Amino acid sequence: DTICIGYHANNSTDTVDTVLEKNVTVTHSVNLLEDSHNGKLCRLKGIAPLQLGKCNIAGWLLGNPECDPLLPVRSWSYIVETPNSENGICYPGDFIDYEELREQLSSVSSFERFEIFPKESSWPNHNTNGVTAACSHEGKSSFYRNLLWLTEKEGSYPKLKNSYVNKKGKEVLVLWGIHHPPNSKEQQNLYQNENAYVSVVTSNYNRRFTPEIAERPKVRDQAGRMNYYWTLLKPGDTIIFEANGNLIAPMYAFALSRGFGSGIITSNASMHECNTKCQTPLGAINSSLPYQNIHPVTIGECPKYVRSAKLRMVTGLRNIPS
Amino acid sequence: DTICIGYHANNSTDTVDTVLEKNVTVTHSVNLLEDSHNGKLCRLKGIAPLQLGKCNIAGWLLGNPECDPLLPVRSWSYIVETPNSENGICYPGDFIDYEELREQLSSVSSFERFEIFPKESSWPNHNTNGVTAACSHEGKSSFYRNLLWLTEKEGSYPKLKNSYVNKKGKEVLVLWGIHHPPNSKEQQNLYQNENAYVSVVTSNYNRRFTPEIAERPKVRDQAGRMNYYWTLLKPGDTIIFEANGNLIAPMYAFALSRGFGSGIITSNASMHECNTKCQTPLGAINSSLPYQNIHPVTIGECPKYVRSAKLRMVTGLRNIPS
Amino acid sequence: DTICIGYHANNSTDTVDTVLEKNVTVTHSVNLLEDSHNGKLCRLKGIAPLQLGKCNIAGWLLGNPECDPLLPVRSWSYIVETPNSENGICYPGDFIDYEELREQLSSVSSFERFEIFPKESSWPNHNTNGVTAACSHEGKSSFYRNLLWLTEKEGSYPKLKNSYVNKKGKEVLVLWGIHHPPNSKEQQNLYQNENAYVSVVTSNYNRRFTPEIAERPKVRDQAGRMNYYWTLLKPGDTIIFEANGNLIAPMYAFALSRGFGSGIITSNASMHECNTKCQTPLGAINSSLPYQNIHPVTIGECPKYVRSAKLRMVTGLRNIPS
Amino acid sequence: XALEYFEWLSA
Amino acid sequence: XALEYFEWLSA
Amino acid sequence: XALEYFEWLSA
Amino acid sequence: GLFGAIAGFIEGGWTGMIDGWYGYHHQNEQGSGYAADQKSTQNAINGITNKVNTVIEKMNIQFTAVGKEFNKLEKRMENLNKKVDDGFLDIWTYNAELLVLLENERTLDFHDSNVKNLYEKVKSQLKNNAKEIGNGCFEFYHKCDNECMESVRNGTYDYPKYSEESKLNRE
Amino acid sequence: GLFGAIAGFIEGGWTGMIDGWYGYHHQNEQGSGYAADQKSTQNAINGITNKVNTVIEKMNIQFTAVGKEFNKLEKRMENLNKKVDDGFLDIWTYNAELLVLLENERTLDFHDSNVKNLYEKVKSQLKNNAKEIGNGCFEFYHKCDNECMESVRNGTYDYPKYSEESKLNRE
Amino acid sequence: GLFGAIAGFIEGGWTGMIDGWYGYHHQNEQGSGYAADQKSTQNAINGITNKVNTVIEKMNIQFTAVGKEFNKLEKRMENLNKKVDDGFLDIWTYNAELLVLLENERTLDFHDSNVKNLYEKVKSQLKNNAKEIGNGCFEFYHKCDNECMESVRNGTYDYPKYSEESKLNRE
Ligand SMILES: *[C@@H]1O[C@H](CO)[C@@H](O[C@@H]2O[C@H](CO)[C@@H](O)[C@H](O)[C@H]2NC(C)=O)[C@H](O)[C@H]1NC(C)=O
Ligand SMILES: *[C@@H]1O[C@H](CO)[C@@H](O[C@@H]2O[C@H](CO)[C@@H](O)[C@H](O)[C@H]2NC(C)=O)[C@H](O)[C@H]1NC(C)=O
Ligand SMILES: *[C@@H]1O[C@H](CO)[C@@H](O[C@@H]2O[C@H](CO)[C@@H](O)[C@H](O)[C@H]2NC(C)=O)[C@H](O)[C@H]1NC(C)=O
Ligand SMILES: *[C@@H]1O[C@H](CO)[C@@H](O)[C@H](O)[C@H]1NC(C)=O
Ligand SMILES: *[C@@H]1O[C@H](CO)[C@@H](O)[C@H](O)[C@H]1NC(C)=O
Ligand SMILES: *[C@@H]1O[C@H](CO)[C@@H](O)[C@H](O)[C@H]1NC(C)=O
Ligand SMILES: *[C@@H]1O[C@H](CO)[C@@H](O)[C@H](O)[C@H]1NC(C)=O
Ligand SMILES: *[C@@H]1O[C@H](CO)[C@@H](O)[C@H](O)[C@H]1NC(C)=O
Ligand SMILES: *[C@@H]1O[C@H](CO)[C@@H](O)[C@H](O)[C@H]1NC(C)=O
Ligand SMILES: [Cl-]
């Protein structure tokens, strides 16, 4: 008569690493590293992303005519730029503090596009019909949907002064541009004053702009430039535009709401009818495990990104069926 | 006859956590996490803080009349701003590189306020009596104690040129401002030149200022602006002021000494007769334990801040009095 | 008859620390902390550093005459500035975005110095022979080897316009300066126009420069200033210079190649005939161990820097020869 | 989390 | 630091 | 890395 | 193992014990079979459940973390920002891989300890009424029926009750 | 525990032993009482003193660390600076909580080991002059007075001196 | 040690055993000498080799890392950049020193375990054909020549072959 003390074995082929020994086959184990994704862009906590299509941030804000227009009001959980954004700034020049604007838009949850300065009504005695071939649409020369190229009318450019009081109860994002012609002949033919200036003020913003005429190497077949500027007009505050030339005026502006947990990602994937708590540029992860090796960029509630190929904890025993 | 081997138990109710088991009662233990503070602002290694009262940094440097004046020389271990600093910049405008000045003042240990440009003596043929209602004091219109609003006198504003050679043997902090009127009428009525300019140079600093006239939305009932500028004049170096209008001149400046371990905190607490080696915005900690969960902001020799609610090391045994 | 079970001892005096006990003598051990260096500047993976001699970065780029000239083409693995760089900017003024240029040069692997604007040929009707005593060489007044002080000729300074198209197939680094005289008399005597301007453009760069006349405290016996500017002209792009005064013109520019793993260090050591995989400002390390306590600055494949004085792992046993 | 490797283990 | 839990422990 | 403390240890 | 049992003086495990980690196999006249010791199995599960949950609990949820952009004159800021992303990733990759190795070591040793503790718990119950025949088994110097085997398994073995019969067979 | 002693085959501890962590209780004709084994207690204190001090020593003093400010056009720099504060705090909260758990485990196991080492040190001194009556006690096959008990406690027990008398009572 | 052997009931080590970490010394009529147990030595080396290599492997190569410069109006950026350098250095100095302490503890305990496992492996082979004379030695109740000693060393000791002779000398 005999009794024996022993331990469990089974048919598991799980392996784990330890300090003293690699590749130990064990009976029961737990994986801590998520490495799978679904290849799709998904809703995040029920809210769809803002997909910019053929545009980048700059092209959507300025109103590039090549990009399909969006509904006047959008809400989103994160913004998706495509890697091959061909449509952005179409008239060459510099977007000032562009990178800080992106960072601001990373915490915006919603916009409402609205006509801040109605076209035929805000700049009397000035031409508003200017277009260019650098910003073409359906072959024809066109212009930014959100801005307006004000030019001379009947051989004069009178000094203008317009202003907007923000009663939207949310920050308003105002964008404008400043044109720089390549020679003083075109400066006269367009704004009739060689010593033009533009002035833009709010309670807290204060900047003045001067034409800088010089020949420049052609970009998109243009020897002049157009710089672009922006400010966030606080609720109740007033923005005043004053100029006697060279101003690319605001026509449409954005009332903005703030949010949490949003972001901008660049992604090759497509939107699908799916929902997730965690989004990467490659696809959505479910978020039960503590680590993930799929992407360092994440939106939402996500595991922590690590370079590991394997993170497996043993729970059972050294498996010896011999 | 018998002998037994055993172990200690006692009346301790200390609990600790381990990897395999939570909440184990043990006989002897050590706490590593300090969680208590005294609620007071204390001296730090024997040196009192600099409390700015109703002012913020900007209001103390410019000489805001609402804040009680300080002794002409102060030494401190850290600077305390109150959360509800109502007195700061009283005439609206922008303080240029304000944030970098704060960072500089975070390593200053001492100041000596001195008259760099005596009032009635440095700007002959100019009026120095200008005041404003935005900077009021006891109801009457007033002005910054450290600056001087130079205006036209007997219908002229002659070009001025003054300079100061630093023989203090320490960095001197010079502050000045530039006024921006809302219309060219007031520009003429105050400085008599529409094309005014201000020039400020040292060995290493070089900046020129131009009035920018435009109507602006009222702030503190003012449609114009006043920008504020500063530089650190090195020992032995000379600062030259040259202007024919619009200059808000320095009257008082600060000789500065450098120190170590100082900081700026925002705090609701009061100064008491106490001394500490570690200060937080909530109160002083003693600094024997390696971790603290009281505040992430610390001055002096402090434990390391952690989010933990409990860090208790067991030294004794699993306590089994049964 | 007896048999005994035992363990190894020997004559090793290695000590290690553990958690429960310090300074345990053991039989076999491994050192993980490299603390030795050879005191020399060495080649890195076969490639020699770029040693700037008596110059700093600023003095080599501007062509300071005191520094020995380099071969027209150099390739390097890292750049060495000496701590006591006496030769840098010799004509006083500000080097704009100097720190960003250093950062750019930290990933450059090679330069080719070339005459972008041949001296006697690019600025007709202007004098090119200007020199100064602040930039002396062998006692005589001299000037930057890479720039050219253009002055008035036969009592005029005609408007100039020159340009360079980059066919080098690599970024070209163009440097120029702008002179600021202390008084309008010298502004006239040198450039014959009090309202001078300089314009510099490429496809993507756009800046305009204006003389700012003011008396300044002498530096290196000069009451005026010279600011210095740069841009990286992309392959195929054109840089246009236009001015009617005050321009310190480019004569020589740098075609640049990018590389990996390079860096700038400040070092007191000398170049020797040696090769290493890891370089510090104190000397070369071999890189077998995981940690080093020699310097936090490293170039190449290096151990990780730690403050530890000792990192010794025990492999053998507690050594008890008693 | 639960290690329910056998049903008699509890939750 | 010292764990002086009993007086005969040393310091 | 190898701990070749004795020759019969293997590499 | 550190405690000598698993893969030690008990060379292998039992595919036949399907209801627990630690247990027994017996052989008497009424028959033979396996039975697991639930009290020690449930202790081990409780400990490893806590170990696994603590490993997950120390890892906070990772909230949104996306790149920034920089212009051509902000390289130093872009390299600092890259240094911060790489540095935190270096550290968390290291922390995760090391914590799992260290806990895997201790988890195997914890099992090995539990087996041996059970073996010694049985050995001290039987004393000289049985003999260690190696490999973690005991041979009884007396007849041990199912009720006797169950008394060993649940820790109530009656040493005097069989001491005489065992003394005789032991001789 | 890992070593089977504390809360194992020695079910509980002694409120009555007030002068040390590890010790003895004896019962003979002259009386009974507790006495602690100072040599093993002092070793344990020395080890745990070093453990605690090393935990404090690896944590450098935290010198001054205060916030910075940023203007409305420096959000990216403000978010980088926040990322650096949170990242270091994430890591140090994790390091501290984990180090204490891991050391608490090893500290309990270290005690459990010390008890068992003492038990086996006594068992090997007595050999067959006494019998293990479980629960960490021994019953002598001979008379053991205070001088005899003291010889067991300080490691000088004389096995031959009582071997005959023990053989007889053992029979 | 945690397992009681090294510096425990085996007070010291053998300068005389020069060919391994763990082994044997024997004394019979043909002579005396030392011989190391290669199977346990090679296991230990394999484990510690892996431990050391894993410690080196978790530490990635450190690629180029040099300072940046800042102008007089970029102090906040310079202090952030200094905070990042110090923070990562604080953490890696801490990680390195702690990992080595923790592994040094476990490495000594691992040896102590290996010695004891070997001792118990021998004890269970001999059973009552020999007697534990303390200090990790056994005295045979029979004659054990070189062939017999070699059978103990390589785990093939024949207990019945000497059981009679041992019973007699044991009496
Ligand atoms: C880790 O261990 C596993 C288990 O032994 C190894 O996988 C086995 O390898 C052998 C040899 O080719 C095969 O006969 C078995 O069928 C494999 N098992 C399974 C489940 O496929 C594996 O090769 C080991 N890896 C390393 C790197 O040591
Ligand atoms: C941790 O353990 C302690 C000690 O057992 C628990 O505190 C005891 O809880 C019981 C049940 O309410 C009371 O009867 C005792 O009086 C408590 N002890 C003391 C000193 O107050 C405690 O509840 C446990 N906590 C957790 C989360 O398990
Ligand atoms: C660490 O241990 C070593 C080894 O015991 C100590 O070095 C010995 O110190 C004694 C006392 O002075 C000398 O007699 C020996 O000759 C030393 N050994 C050697 C190899 O030099 C050392 O002092 C200890 N250090 C600490 C801080 O405890
Ligand atoms: C183990 O065996 C069972 C059959 O009882 C089977 O269902 C299961 O898939 C097997 N596991 C593996 C990993 O093959
Ligand atoms: C998505 O974008 C990447 C660029 O990172 C590209 O290499 C990849 O091929 C794209 N996917 C497909 C399916 O083309
Ligand atoms: C333990 O008992 C003592 C009385 O000897 C008492 O002084 C002490 O306060 C008690 N400890 C606790 C935690 O109650
Ligand atoms: C101190 O300031 C805080 C603001 O952070 C405020 O909420 C708190 O109420 C203040 N303390 C008192 C006593 O009012
Ligand atoms: C140990 O002894 C040997 C002689 O066999 C000698 O070669 C070696 O240097 C000694 N080691 C030390 C550390 O002294
Ligand atoms: C090298 O430079 C350092 C400055 O950090 C200086 O203190 C040191 O003396 C120099 N070396 C020599 C040999 O002078
Ligand atoms: Cl451990």
Image (cartoon, coloured by chain):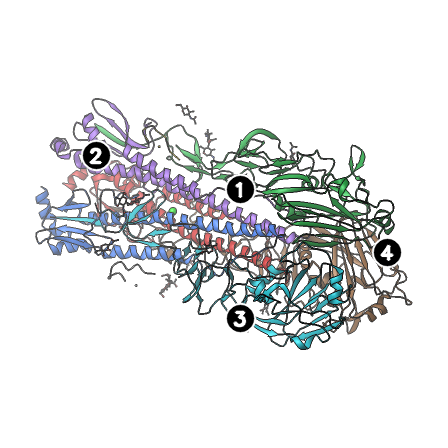
Chain colours: A brown, B green, C cyan, D orange, E yellow, G red, H purple, I blue
Q: Could you classify mark 4 by the number of other residues whose Cα lies within 10 Å: few (under 14), some (14-19), or many (20 or more)?
A: some
Which numbered dot is residue H155?
2
The residue to which callout 1 is attached is B307
Which numbered dot is residue I134?
none
Residue at (57% x, 56% y) in the render: I69
Query: Can you give x and y, in whole percent of width and height, for residue B113 in the image?
Result: 67, 39
- Residues indicated by labels 1 and 4 sit on the same polypeptide chain: no
Measure the alpha-carbon separation of dots 3 and 2.
Answer: 82 Å
The quadrant where residue G47 appears: top left
Identity of the amino acid at label 2? Gly
- Asked if marks 1 and 2 touch (Cβ < 8 Å), the reply is no
Query: Can you give x and y, in whole percent of width and height, for residue I55 in the image?
Result: 39, 55
Q: Secondary structure at mark 1?
A: loop
- Residues indicated by labels 3 and 4 sit on the same polypeptide chain: no
Q: Residue furthest right?
A: A154
Measure the alpha-carbon separation of dots 3 and 4.
Answer: 59 Å
Chain letter for the residue marked with disc 2 in the picture: H
Q: Secondary structure at mark 4?
A: strand
Identity of the amino acid at label 1? Arg
- Residues indicated by labels 4 and 2 sit on the same polypeptide chain: no
Measure the alpha-carbon separation of dots 4 and 2.
Answer: 103 Å
Identity of the amino acid at label 3? Leu
The residue to which callout 3 is attached is C70
Left-right relation of A81 to A191: left
The answer to which of A207 and A67 lies nearer the viewer is: A207
